[PDB]
Length: 49
Length: 49
Image 1 (cartoon, rainbow over the protein chains, first blue to last red):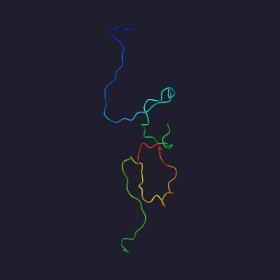
Image 2 (cartoon, rainbow over the protein chains, first blue to last red; image 1 turned 90 degrees about the vertical axis):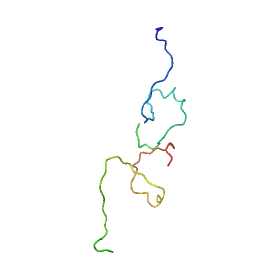
Image 3 (cartoon, one colour; image 1 turned 30 degrees about the vertical axis):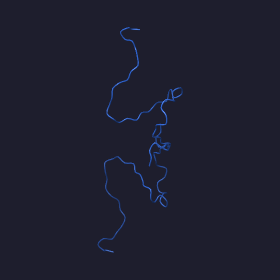
């Protein structure tokens, strides 16, 4: 606890526009009910991971 | 029939490399059994056409 650094909740700075955003293979299990149906799926195996 | 231009069967010249290649919506019907299973499918509707 450092009273000169009380921690809180915020957001950060921006980029040049080219971005869809992925995930990895670890905590899919509790953490899966935020977004909604917002994908550009391809269920045909041409990809791999 | 122009005997100075007898027609035959050949191929053409090349480009810089960025190319997968699509199709349209017209003669899918007789013409569908050349290639094989060579796609990077996405059966999830995120695309549209």
